[PDB]
Image 1 (cartoon, rainbow, N blue to C red):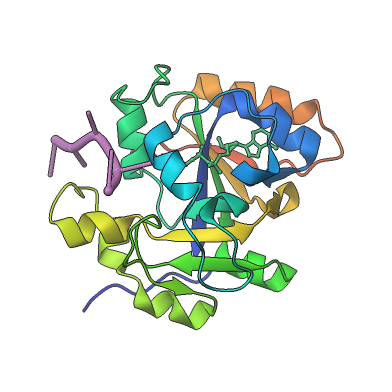
Image 2 (image 1 turned 90 degrees about the vertical axis):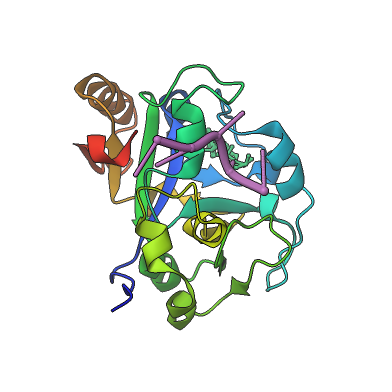
Length: 209
DNA sequence: ATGTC
């Protein structure tokens, strides 16, 4: 009766469109501790500071800031904080891209990864290395459109897929966007990097608030 | 409904 994970299992990384040039110039997403040439932070600083010191207890270890973060859903709680202007960033959701890949693409590429069953800064989050352990996650919570309550559902919606240090651009399969205007601006940027993969750019308003 | 905790 409880939902299982789709296979392939989508993973989602949100970023401001003002960072896409830097992603294509580096040819990869870089983890926070790898000093990405980001133009626009859409994070909470006070939770960023927790990620900065949160130990990852599975090899290859380090801290959460050593990994490129993905969720297993679009339309994240983080995106709600952005949509509602609760962040220092005041631009709203419209310039926020969903970069899409899959857990299985990462495994087949032989990149080191870990994943969690819930918001990764929580002291009781479980960490996993084996894709069979996707069965440990709560796929009802991950897909829930109303996630404010109950508390367990809220935590488990924010299970993370964590790729150590860097995520190659070549593994991104789709860029989802809010609006035609932002789609067009993404294709203009991609065309400045003709050697790079050009993933399909899809308007998915249902991935936004 | 939901302002990542």
